[PDB]
Picture 1: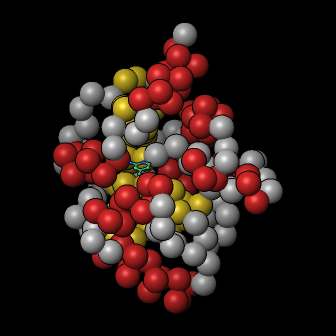
Picture 2 (picture 1 turned 45 degrees about the vertical axis):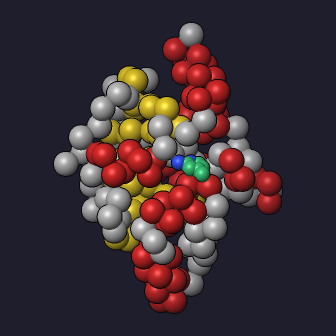
Length: 168
Ligand SMILES: Cc1ccnc(N)c1
């Protein structure tokens, strides 16, 4: 139903909210929820771990089956799997892990995947354990994505930094 509420306009197609993406997915019933995945689709922490836990491991079992056919995703790549109880679809996107020296230029590639979907509930890509500056990631999102993005940021302090950087 894509019943988004309380999202702040950043650009005509990028909105942001201080919220837990799992709780958003349950309220919003989005067509697409984006996971911040790794190449092995192993949902062991951060957004991925949260989304998987909210599916009671339905997402991890489906992810294992895909990886059985595909082998690992490429950095900057994506796949579309079931959203289970969270969404119609989950778009698993692999941003670069800058801690492992993966090129930050692949962040644009990662966000380009969003352009295959009209409306998405998403996190910022390559933030947290992937080591990219989250405000940088928001700039790449805004520059790259032309479809409608509703970004969920869990931490209030980071949310206020992002909004201050973007609008002040
Ligand atoms: C634990 C956790 C980390 C990041 N985003 C969330 N929604 C939840």
